[PDB]
Image (tube, coloured by chain):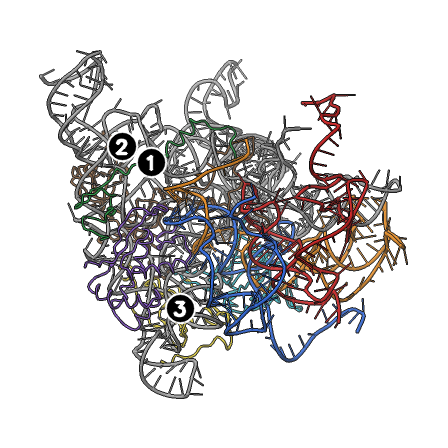
Chain colours: A brown, B cyan, C purple, D yellow, E green, G orange, H blue, I red
Amino acid sequence: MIGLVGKKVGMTRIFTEDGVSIPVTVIEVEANRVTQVKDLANDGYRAIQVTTGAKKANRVTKPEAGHFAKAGVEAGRGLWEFRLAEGEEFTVGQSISVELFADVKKVDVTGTSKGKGFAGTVKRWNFRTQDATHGNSLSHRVPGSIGQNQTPGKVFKGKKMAGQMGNERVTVQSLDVVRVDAERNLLLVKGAVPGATGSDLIVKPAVKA
Amino acid sequence: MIQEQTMLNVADNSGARRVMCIKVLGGSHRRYAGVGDIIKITIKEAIPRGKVKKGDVLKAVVVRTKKGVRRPDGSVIRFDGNACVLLNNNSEQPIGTRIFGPVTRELRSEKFMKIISLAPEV
Amino acid sequence: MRHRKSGRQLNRNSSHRQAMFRNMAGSLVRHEIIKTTLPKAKELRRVVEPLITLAKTDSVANRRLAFARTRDNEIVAKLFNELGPRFASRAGGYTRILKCGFRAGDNAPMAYIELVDRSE
Amino acid sequence: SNIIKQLEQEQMKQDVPSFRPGDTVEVKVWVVEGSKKRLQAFEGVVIAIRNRGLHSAFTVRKISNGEGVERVFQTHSPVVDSISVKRRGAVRKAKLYYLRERTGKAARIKERLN
Amino acid sequence: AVQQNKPTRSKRGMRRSHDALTAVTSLSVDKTSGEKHLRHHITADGYYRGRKVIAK
RNA sequence: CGAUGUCGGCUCAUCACAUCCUGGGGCUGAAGUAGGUCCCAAGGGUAUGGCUGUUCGCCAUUUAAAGUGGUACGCGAGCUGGGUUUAGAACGUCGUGAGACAGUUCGGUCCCUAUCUGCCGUGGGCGCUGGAGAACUGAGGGGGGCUGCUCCUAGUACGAGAGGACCGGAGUGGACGCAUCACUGGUGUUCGGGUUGUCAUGCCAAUGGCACUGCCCGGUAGCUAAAUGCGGAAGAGAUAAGUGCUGAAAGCAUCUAAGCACGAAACUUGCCCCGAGAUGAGUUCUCCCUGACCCUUUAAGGGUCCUGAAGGAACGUUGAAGACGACGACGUUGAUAGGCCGGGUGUGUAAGCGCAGCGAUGCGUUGAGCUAACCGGUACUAAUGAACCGUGAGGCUUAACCU
RNA sequence: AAUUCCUUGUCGGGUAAGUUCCGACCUGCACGAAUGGCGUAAUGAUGGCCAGGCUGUCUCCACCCGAGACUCAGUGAAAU
RNA sequence: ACACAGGUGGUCAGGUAGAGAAUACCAAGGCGCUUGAGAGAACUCGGGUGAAGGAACUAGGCAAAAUGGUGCCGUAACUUC
RNA sequence: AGGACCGAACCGACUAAUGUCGAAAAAUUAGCGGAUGACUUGUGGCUGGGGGUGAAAGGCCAAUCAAACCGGGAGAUAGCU
């Protein structure tokens, strides 16, 4: 089934009547407007493309402005589309609310993780550091050996080395949905989700049922 | 957070006063023992008249930790020292007759009934 | 990675950085316009403009607190007597930065920082 | 944020008494043993208070039979029922962490008498 | 740590292909004095956005 | 031999299967639990310490197991230098002696700024053919694949008893990986406070400089673990060893020759990520350009004037984005940054004055004063009008429908 | 044993675990009395072993402050 | 070999605290060391702090951490006293 | 009184890190030993190469020592590259 696009809004905890406190991530899921519906006849697959939020009138380009005007949908920030499960249908211009998550229990949240920049092997791949004393010289956090000898004669592809860490989309799956608030457009999910505050997130029902 | 080579006090009156943890049981490559995990210890100094002598290896259960324990609502319990209770290596069965100091309720595993009963508090 | 951190280091230690802003804040008040590098000028807005805000209301405690910064009785006199009343109705933004090319010695991006005054 | 702050506000409790570090406090907490619910009393000295709104918490240290016990209570958790103040320590430090090292006659503090 | 064969002038030029400078090609004309200057920068004589700012 | 650095340890691994564990089976001198042996199986996992330079080995205590080998007995332009293997010295022994001894002890310089291949990241150029802005399909590639214990079944089957299942379900752990900062904490030389010596601001009071942040006590935001959530699947397809149904050759029998069934953490998919430079360069949606002159070696030709749109770039303010590029937001039709207002947080009752005391000091004003990166607002300052790049309806052949 | 190949001799002490160390025996391969033998208080930047305190040595690293590394302007090498 | 973190004999040598020519901060006097400006990655160098544990590291407590002054009390084995 | 004790100048160089095309053809930083003596140091002398000097390492004798440096025999010789 289709997901929804929301914005991460900090974190909080919910106190239950029995005493236990549930850490919850707050996701602001306002109305999602369908801008385009894809069908097997034309696109070879069925999907719905949705938009959310708002954009400055002078900031949206003409190609994007015409695309929204065709669907009669107010311009929003970015576009995302979700594949259909063959059991439901949608129409252009339809608005989708967070209420569809009322009957679900597990969700999958996808977002861009925080960017750590160029990271070393110790931080990136949990490499073990070498001794800080006992004669060690300029080799306290160095990766160490990266190959065997002449017989391979090369470093194998996929070697773990320092490089860019974070700033890629990652998915946290099977997260418990704690509360849904349609009128206030909130979705409380137990746990933590990728990305920093204000980052766009995609929420869909858990697939590992 | 009890790991190998850690000093522990003895809550019971078995005659031991200070013990060394030499192994954390319950899993391969386990790092440190929790609130109520079984550990293997060696006695470093005990009462001469006690039933347990120095330099003997026997199991033990942690009852108090300096690091503390976490409650489901976010509360924590912390102590000024680490304490344990002695065992029999074949059946858990704390050999002590009385245990001093508070004991947390995390040990209620349908089994440590003897420990909790002897506990002056909780 | 300095996420959400603020405050330029300017290749100086804390003590040197604090003194340099202290002097160069005092110079700006004295002359009402100075020429510096762009990074230095931007960081000064956060140490000079608070001083003018303090000078808005004249009091013994404020005078002592103002003196503890810039450690100059001339500057303290200049504040509370001219800068204070001049900016009485001004809600911040007492400074203005104007880029003025590059320094010949090392090609440092240079800029003029000057109070919103001197319209005589 | 506005959304978060509004969300936490509805979970507050307005019956939180005003207390300061160094004040002797007895905090009543709920205890559950299978199906029975009881009230347990924890009396001690507040050595640190953390103010963060719904996340505010304080820690209480008491001298038990042999060693001290430090417990951190979440102020707005349902587990805590009531907080009562007996003494008013005349300390002038936000965090009384130095009391851990001290013991005996050196762990006592004066009375505010205000 | 050191080369086994001296790179050719072809490789040298190929590496240097990215060292070319770029012209500003963005010179704005002052509103009043009509003096060419870098964008968002004061003119040589001390004008900016028309009004004189240096007075020196 | 115009030089291929040698034993161990550390870091980092990768492959084989003659499999240590987990998985599937045959036989058993297999009652059950637990075994013995053989076959299939390399997906993942596959200890910590004491002694010794040791590999090894002995010993202590864990685990489901602490597998065997290849890779210059893997890995010193990655680290160490304990052993061995220079020069000093001593012991035993051999020699008249200099000296020697896989005999033993004490001490004893480990260089290299990476051109190429390789690998981990990140960009520019051009191409994909009229240009441009978006959203995708997915060839293909990679990541992950571990498991203990407790309870129910059940104290059931089995067994004289003692002992004690298979299959299936639930809960809770260890190790490993991803994400995050709500909680518990670390850090917090940009916040507050205490205090020692000394110099200075005319002096008292009050402050600042220096002494590792002078030494300390707390601590915001960020980053972060010890903290907190989540993951290993289920299912499907074709199979290995193995078990079969029907069934002739060979009137019988026979799992096989025809045909039809099941059958493992292996294989393909399912889960997550990259991905159209996939030159086989893909699909969809939207936007922009439809003015004239001439020249010839009349060609997908060249030249001139006028127009240059969509959009892009550049510049500026910048960012939970970042080595630099890149990426995201904003540029007044404006909350992008700074300041300012209010709040929060932290530290903790400022200075001044008054009162009590001979004084240090105490009390009142006063939970005051000051507060970095946080929250909500506010055009006060800075994000300038413009210039620059990018054009003018987009080749040939053929096929199908209008004409 | 600064001497011992067999050897980690045998027993005891110390450790949960001791090829090291300490004590005792002598089967001294191959100690031995001024190329001196056995003791010896004090002394030693001398060898070995153990204990208390102490700690980022380590389980397991995290953050922070400075100088380089990175970008811009000027100058401008080296082995090969 | 250099406008080189090295070496080079003698004399004068103030204030506050201090036993002191140690050490900290200063006077007279002399200097900021002849490339700068930014950014605030890995990693290297020199430092600061650290939850729980406290040598489990390692050939080896290497390196770090710790102890550190004055006065009074008290101070073992052994000994050439 | 002391080849006495602690500790600066001064003399020396036990450990670690940095530095190895370095700031330096043995240094820097933090610790470390002696520091009234068999001490250390300025100036000037004497000992000359199969010789000197040596609290003895084959150490030192102008950054060179199991026989210094310079010139000569000398185009030594080289069954070797």
Residue A45: mark: 2
Mark toward the viewer: 1 or 3: 1
- Would you place residue D17 above or below residue G24 in this image? below
Q: Kindly identify which residue carries mark 1.
A: E21
Residue G38 position by quadrant: bottom right
Residue D7, image x, y percentages:
28, 58
Residue D98, image x, y percentages:
47, 70
Q: Residue at x 37, y 35 (%)?
A: E19
Q: Chain of mark 3?
A: D
Q: Are marks 1 and 3 on the same chain?
A: no
Residue B81: mark: none
Of the residues shown, which amino acid type is indicated by label 1?
A: Leu
Disc 1 to disc 3, how far (Cα)? 79 Å
Within 10 Å of disc 1 (Cα), the crowding (few <14, some 14-19, many 20+) is few
User: SS at mark 1?
Assistant: loop
Q: Residue at x 31, y 58 (%)?
A: C46
- Would you place residue G50 above or below residue H45 in this image? below
Within 10 Å of disc 2 (Cα), the crowding (few <14, some 14-19, many 20+) is few
Disc 1 to disc 2, how far (Cα)? 48 Å
Q: Chain of mark 1?
A: E
Q: Kindly identify which residue carries mark 3.
A: D38
Of the residues shown, which amino acid type is indicated by label 2?
A: Tyr
Of the residues shown, which amino acid type is indicated by label 3?
A: Arg
Q: Are marks 2 and 3 in contact (CB under 8 Å)?
A: no
Q: Are marks 1 and 2 in contact (CB under 8 Å)?
A: no
User: Is residue A30 visible to the viewer in this orientation of the structure?
Assistant: yes
The quarter of the image holding the C terminus of chain C is: bottom left
